[PDB]
Image (cartoon, rainbow, N blue to C red; front, side, top):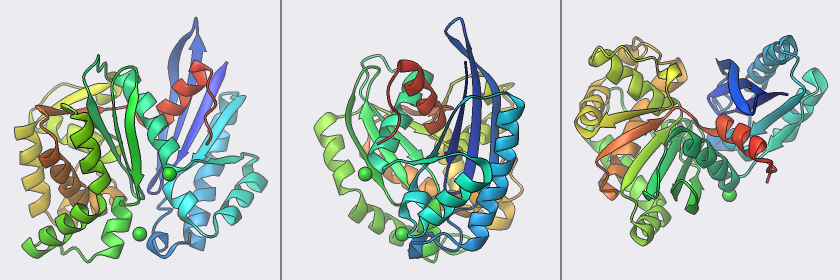
Amino acid sequence: QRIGVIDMGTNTFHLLITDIVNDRPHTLVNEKSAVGLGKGGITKGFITEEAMDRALDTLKKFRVILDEHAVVHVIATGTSAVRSGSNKQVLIDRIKKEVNIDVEVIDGAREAELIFRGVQQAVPMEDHISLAMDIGGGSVEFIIGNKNEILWKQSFEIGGQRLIDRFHVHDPMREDDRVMMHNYFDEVLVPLEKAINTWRPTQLIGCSGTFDTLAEMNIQHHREKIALEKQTSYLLSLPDFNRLRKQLVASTRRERLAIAGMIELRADMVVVAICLIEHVLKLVSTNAITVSTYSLKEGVLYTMLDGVKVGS
Ligand SMILES: [Cl-]
Ligand SMILES: [Cl-]
């Protein structure tokens, strides 16, 4: 039948609708909407009224699109901003009343697992031990695995909206800001360092909006005739990453707002995100970065198609 998946992310909500004919899935809708669920509240442990109202607006629109495609099987996941918010049940109950969708709140571990199922479908890793990283506005998930297995995974509440709200990063970034961020990452990421030492991944994979934007910027810079919508991976060399890093660290918020595809909430957090990627790169001896165009919503879909329960 047709399957609809909603990812209620901290910055951006996503809607994926897939038809599955002759056991082959085909995308009917892949839509996003900037919601800013974390704005004004995430580091203080709540969701604001304005953010809840934006969320409901977007969900009313997504409900129309679901109905316009006669979708029967729907699953809507709530992740970092939803699970973190003391008033999450207010939002969940408003959603049920307004559009008759039940939000499935998933913890960080399960979010990481589901993301990696999407990565496995997008990037054929063979037996290569790989570190995948998903940077969102609220959390960052890290998974070590290969085509068949997850060896280790962990979610950390260090998504970009949290980072820019908890710390004062200057516009543009200063040397002392770089010290601040990498010192913080040193403290937070100890379990990641330990896992990397244990499993020795040899490749780095990134997914979600920050990585999609880096890919799109690189495509434009090299004048590549590549629609990222029509392929499931994109390899970014380390020299290309370092060009983008230098460009974005030097940039102002206003300059970033002018980059094609760089939505406002991503412009706000992309510099701290690139600092985190650099930090992780120094821990791995990868040869390049592979961007997976699949992330949580695709992992949910493929988990469903596998015949496996999504929640937990
Ligand atoms: Cl926080
Ligand atoms: Cl967890």
